[PDB]
Length: 238
Ligand SMILES: [Hg+2]
Ligand SMILES: [Hg+2]
Image (cartoon, rainbow, N blue to C red; front, side):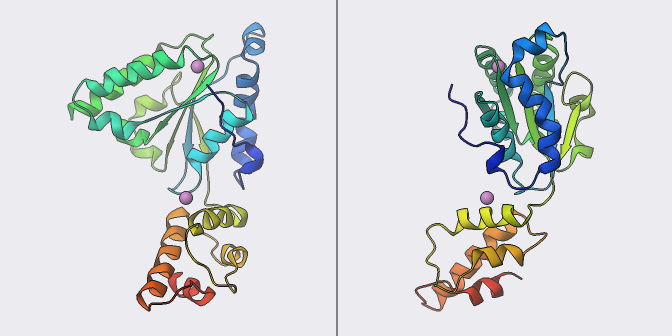
């Protein structure tokens, strides 16, 4: 019931995405206004971009910026459940979401569902739940993927995820943020400059930054060293 603490001011980069999401935010902040105005918002937004680019974080920031609940679920989990259970769970998800107007329902790993009885049954239920939305339903469904081209076309038809928003690799601030988060718990030498590390890793995604630190940690750990140095980070980079 408590909206996330994360807001747009906490999201580095994604400047274009934020612009395109302004409309969703304003709707979530005052759904009654858009209803009375007879306006019409998507209700289905797909964030497109590579893994470790901050897609989930941004979606959470939308709920935070609008100070509205952020209800999460995983397409992966749904499909892992017994045949029919994933569908039943999809059903439970939207029934619960409807008791919290307005809100954001975020389906993680939509690829698992949109890309086998389990998957199909889960997908058909999601399709039905989305078509089941009335123009008055104060719900915005968000999802994320990097391969929108191999996604079941049905998920992109009008009334569903008919709004896509590109999310590129993190900018220098995004990378620094990712690096600082993953550096927690790792002993760094005084000469370690995470800000410089971010500047010198343009194009890197969350996974690369994570393996860079882990690989630096392993080197220092293997050589029996007590602290990770800037050189270790530079060596682990490639
Ligand atoms: Hg809702
Ligand atoms: Hg991360």
